[PDB]
Image: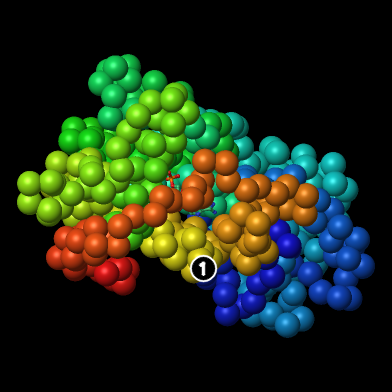
Amino acid sequence: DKIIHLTDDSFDTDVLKADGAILVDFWAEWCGPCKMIAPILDEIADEYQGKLTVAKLNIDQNPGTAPKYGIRGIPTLLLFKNGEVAATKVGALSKGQLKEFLDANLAAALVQQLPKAIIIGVRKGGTRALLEMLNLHPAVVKASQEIHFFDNDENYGKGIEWYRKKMPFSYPQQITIEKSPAYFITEEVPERIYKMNSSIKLLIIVREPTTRAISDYTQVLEGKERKNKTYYKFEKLAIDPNTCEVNTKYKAVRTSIYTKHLERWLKYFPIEQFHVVDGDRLITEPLPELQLVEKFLNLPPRISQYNLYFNATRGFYCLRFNEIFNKCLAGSKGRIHPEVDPSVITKLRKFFHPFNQKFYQITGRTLNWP
Ligand SMILES: Nc1ncnc2c1ncn2[C@@H]1O[C@H](COP(=O)(O)O)[C@@H](OP(=O)(O)O)[C@H]1O
């Protein structure tokens, strides 16, 4: 239910310490009009998702708050804009009367905003899955395609205004998020993002290093199988034949060394502006990982178990927004990996181990890979 039921205990957290526009309805079971506008409020919460949050406060069970604002009779509607009464309305009113009161008081013009958080990587970590799942939140709009702005000198030269006009439209209250997995490893990107928005928030979703490398390789092989071209076995690319050790020049191994790349980014951004998503837990138990991202982005908790249903035939979780809109990810997500010689997997696990430890230390998240 899109409506938020308040208590006197949780009014500071949910309205005053909150951000965005919130309409609070003060009501009680003995107020006829209050029960006559309850259906209207239900339709408003749905037609104004994005630009307004509708909340109720039952003054019978919560007698503390209403006096603090001069609430004489009920119903009384208080529109808060970022913990500050911006408007009031007293006594019942029609759905069209409420729409006139809101529309003439909400800054709800559709706008193209620069992203306030960027998923900077990693390739095959679950970037698409992370983006689509965060979009489940009513405050988040996703950039549908990968934009590739800071990692492409042709695009970067077109100005930050070009980047902005690539973004989707949104109510100014929402936040926009973009995904471009190449940003993580491209050298010039951290300083360019920093110039744009030195306080931007950066998301990194990682998987088990060896597994991410094989997933990487598998994507390249599909695109080569399709074109009827020859490639090589993962074992031949990942192991140097002269030493039988890990070949550090292989791009898919280089990209799983998450800590060498992160340290380039820490030259410019503090660790407090990063959040690391456990891409493995996103595959098997995603909801807790999404709740951490909600708090990282200073968003209220709106993603629930209802929004994630497991698809047994697919082997992955799928998304459910409302009662009728359902979505699984594209066909290229969830490829079966080739079987890889166990000895090589052991050599890679032993190879990544010290880099994993350094990664846990810097980020403060221990992901329990080998
Ligand atoms: N709900 C989901 N559906 C499909 N793949 C998902 C998923 N949640 C996470 N993933 C993972 O994200 C990978 C794709 O990442 P990206 O979008 O960054 O390329 C998938 O690659 P695999 O084919 O290796 O399983 C899979 O491991």
What quarter of the picture does the C terminus occupy? bottom left
Residue 312 position within the rendered picture, expressed as x and y whole percent measured from the top left:
65, 61
Above or below: residue 343 compared with residue 148: below
Seen in the picture, residue 4 relative to 53 is either above or below; the reply is: below
Q: Secondary structure at mark 1?
A: loop
For label 1, the crowd category at 10 Å Cα-Cα, with few meaning under 14, some 14 to 19 and many 20 or more, is some
Q: Residue at x 63, y 41 (%)?
A: 106
Task: Determine the residue positioned at 38% across, 26% down.
Answer: 229
Classify residue 39 as left or right of residue 286. Answer: right
Task: Identify the residue at the far left of this view.
Answer: 243
Residue 369 in sight = yes
Q: Is residue 129 visible?
A: no
Q: Position of residue 367 (x, y in %)?
A: 32, 68
Left or right? Give the position of 191 relative to 154.
left
The quarter of the image holding the N terminus is bottom right
Q: Position of residue 158 (x, y in %)?
A: 32, 17
Is ligand 1 less than 8 Å from the beta carbon at label 1? Answer: no
Q: Amino acid at mark 1?
A: Glu
Q: On screen, 49 above or below 208? A: above
Q: Quadrant of residue 366?
A: bottom left
- Give the residue pinned by disc 1: 285
